[PDB]
Image (tube, rainbow over all chains, first blue to last red; front, top):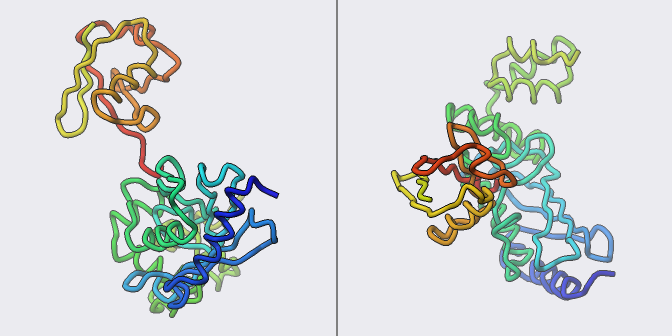
Length: 201
Length: 76
């Protein structure tokens, strides 16, 4: 249904990922949404020695019909705390997804670069300013905050409960635990200003 | 005429321009001298950006006036 230099590239790049050593080791993975191959669901495992370790992140991959001369539009379906990824929408700030895309890049190399992006964030050049300045000003707070998002959203081992007690305390006020994890983390785990931010209207 | 573009790294870029010129073309001859893509760079004068459609004399940038180049964010 596409111009096929996409259909042929996508089909062999798709078949390239399932045959790879990274899929055999469960690092990356790609799947079919429909069977025209213009939308794919990718999955990358959180890199080791990073707060995302033990987590698996779903990725929305939409192949434009200018493929392979324009990059695929990738968005994080799974929530993640990362200065180069939106904590709200999952938008990705990577140059290979914008100006620095090359036609030689494949599905595998895009997934491997995104998995690499989790290991090496660029806070000076961010997608989420809130996550980025917490990353710079408080390195340890970001690490466990990303660790907590890593379990609540990507099924990792739990971050240790010095942070959940607040998540417990604000829920004792009947608040949405989804709104509380967002409010507490953006306000750098200050319950006061989180409670003041907690209320929309 | 001669204008300057002070940059990161204490670099000083010297360009021969006309007040007639787009800010886009000022970016274009920074590209030939520095190998910097024009839509990843932004020039500030009097501490203000100048949109590519406008020209330098609209911002009364006379000769020997100093500009500063902040480069657009990577991702970005």
